[PDB]
Amino acid sequence: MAQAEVLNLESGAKQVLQETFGYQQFRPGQEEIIDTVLSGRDCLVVMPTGGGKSLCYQIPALLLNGLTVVVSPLISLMKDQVDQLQANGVAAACLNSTQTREQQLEVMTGCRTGQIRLLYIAPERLMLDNFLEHLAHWNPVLLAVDEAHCISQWGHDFRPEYAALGQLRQRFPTLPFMALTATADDTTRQDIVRLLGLNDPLIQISSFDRPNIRYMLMEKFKPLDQLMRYVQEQRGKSGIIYCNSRAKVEDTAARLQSKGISAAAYHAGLENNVRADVQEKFQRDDLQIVVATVAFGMGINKPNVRFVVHFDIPRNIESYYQETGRAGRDGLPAEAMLFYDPADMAWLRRCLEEKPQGQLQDIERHKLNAMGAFAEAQTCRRLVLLNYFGEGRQEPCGNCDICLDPPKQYDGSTDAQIALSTIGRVNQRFGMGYVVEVIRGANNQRIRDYGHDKLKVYGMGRDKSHEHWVSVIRQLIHLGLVTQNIAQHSALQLTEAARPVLRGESSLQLAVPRIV
Ligand SMILES: [Mn+2]
Ligand SMILES: [Zn+2]
């Protein structure tokens, strides 16, 4: 079998980091994870980038005797990891249904004979053709599940092939598991641990704050002209412009090229050699801009992308966070610019509400609502993101469009106490609409049947508009005082941070709600 490379495991982690991978020091959370994995304890890793993430299982794999198995759905990216690893002297291979059976059998023979240390496998392949019975004889020492949020229906990218990964724990009870992801909120993180059967795992959630990325929004008004001007104002800085159609990509690349800008189109309709060339030309800074569909995702992630534009709003914050997160991997100042029109959200809502009714549509609706609320926020954009992912923070960043031009404020302490009290009084079971009706004292049969018309809070906000109360509550959500529980039909629920305001111990400044 693949042999451990270092005598002392504790000192080995840093030795391999530096000597094999060339990194001088660990990033936050990495050492902890790696030492925990080397101790044989299950782990869930929520990390800012794939880069720090992958070393969380590659370093352990080099310090252990045995085979490390890495499950990933990214076939054309898994194959790239292998080449890069092999170039660093690491015995890596991959197995998936796209390979010929001849090639698959060679990889299986490499694992059987102990010539392969690290095997990347597609989830479908791992659970097919009695592969697990073969895997049991190959001295498995660690099983890592990448893109682990894909096992959850509460996430933004559920994959049916991940569901069967819940059978691994039972089949390999003494095999330590790790689950890894860059984008999972609280509900999704909890679901990952439950579905994979992680045994009291170390849960390492790194910060979602990328302090060097400035987040901005521009309301659309002749948006093709706004986009060209934005690009002109970058004055040569590199960028990715994300569009939701191939024609937008192609037309946008042509208009930029017409103005002397070094830009290329990138989408799944290009040939593989053309895709690789565009990626390489962008990596080396031969190209200033790549205009792309969501296909030009992570994977290339040049460290020095200066800006990411979203011409069209994404369907969920998870996607928006992942895509904007491709900017400024080097830590130098970077910007994310989203062009928005409320008619864009109206269209997405239309598309969604005629899809099949039920649980799946509810999940999509919840995440779409939150994306629209981010766009229409009156609170620091960074706080919206951080609190969406459950990273409690109330201090404004000073580095987003809202922080650069804060809305007029008012003392919202009384309004916040009314909203927070209402949420508590209705036992945190109801969504935004119902709560606002209770506050405004509406004539509603449902309210009377629950007896909520007898509450003291009932009608305490009747003198302020529906949109006023929606804004108050949305700002409380964006500040992390209130959450929307996706597993309870988006019920409004209270956090620990709500306590001082609810008690009247602290004052709360809020944005005066926009008239709209
Ligand atoms: Mn250590
Ligand atoms: Zn801010």
Image: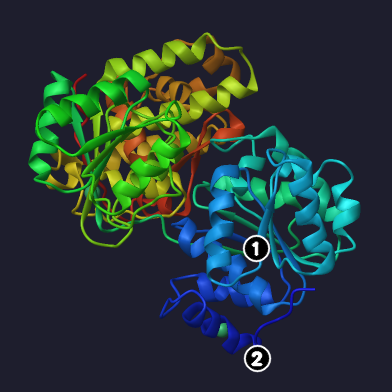
Q: Is residue 328 visible to the viewer in this orientation of the structure?
A: yes
Q: CA distance from mark 1 to mark 2?
A: 23 Å
- Closer to the camera, 402 or 217? 217
Identify the secondary structure beneath mark 2. Answer: loop
Q: Position of residue 104 (x, y in %)?
A: 76, 48
| Image position of 511 with respect to 3: above or below | above
Q: Nearer the viewer, residue 102 or 405?
A: 102
Residue 31 in picture, x, y percent from top left: 53, 76
Vertical placement of residue 108 versus 238, above or below: below
According to the picture, the residue beneath numbered tag 2 turns out to be 8
Q: Mark 1 falls on what kind of element?
A: strand
**Would you say 492 lies left or right of 512 here?**
right
Q: Which residue type does callout 2 highlight?
A: Asn
Q: Answer above or below: position of 270 versus 163.
A: above
Quarter of the image for residue 461 reads top left
Numbered disc in front, either 1 or 2:
1
Q: Earlier in the sequence, mark 1 or mark 2?
A: 2
Q: Is residue 169 left or right of residue 10?
A: right
**Residue underneath mark 1:** 92
**Neighbourhood count class around disc 2 (C-alpha, 10 Å): few under 14, some 14–19, many 20 upward:** few
Tell me the kind of residue under disc 1. Ala
User: Residue 22, percent across and down?
Assistant: 44, 77
Q: Quadrant of ligand 1?
A: bottom right
* Residue at 54% over, 48% down: 77
